[PDB]
Image (tube, coloured by chain):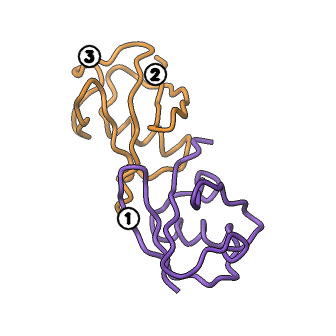
Chain colours: A orange, B purple
Amino acid sequence: MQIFVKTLTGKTITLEVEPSDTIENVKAKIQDKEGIPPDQQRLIFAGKQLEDGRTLSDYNIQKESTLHLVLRLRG
Amino acid sequence: MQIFVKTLTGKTITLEVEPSDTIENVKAKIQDKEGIPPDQQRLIFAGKQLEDGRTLSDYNIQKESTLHLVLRLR
């Protein structure tokens, strides 16, 4: 399925994910597509900071939902 | 010299740079520190987006200046 990923600047990309992906898998797919380390990715949906071990579908993330990405600057 | 680099939420790093460092060099220094690819970085100084082949001193970025970093999602 396709979701959107959006930063605080409004920049938006599309990302192919599976509903059964863990958040870690989602961050890995962002890293593959964009080169951003997973530990640098804070992903937010509907108020909540998304946790790596949880699954997208369990957060009721939907087809064409948008995750918000914030840069962590962890290094 | 030291400069600061900040995200839109206020996350801050320092970098060791020279006035003659190109913007490409500085992005590569950020990649070294943070793992972020240079072509994924946009750096801004006091409203002005910094261009890869120019140097810090071109923008009158002196010691202890702050730059802001955003992702390009390129």
In the displayed structure, does residue A49 sit left or right of residue A18? left
> What's the residue type where badge 2 is placed?
Ile
Residue identifier under label 3: A60
Residue located at (50% from left, 25% from top): A16
Q: Name the disc covering residue B20, or none.
A: none
Residue located at (67% from left, 78% from top): B21
Q: Mark 1–mark 2 contact, CB under 8 Å?
A: no
Mark 3 to mark 1 CA distance (whole Å)? 33 Å
Residue identifier under label 1: B12
Which of B2 and A27 lies nearest the eye of the viewer? B2
Residue located at (45% from left, 64% from top): B34
In the displayed structure, does residue A34 sit left or right of residue B57? left
Residue located at (54% from left, 26% from top): A14
> What's the residue type where badge 1 is placed?
Thr
Q: Are marks 3 and 1 on the same chain?
A: no
Which of A59 and B67 lies nearest the eye of the viewer? B67
Which of A27 and B13 lies nearest the eye of the viewer? B13
Please give the chain letter of the residue carrying mark 1.
Answer: B
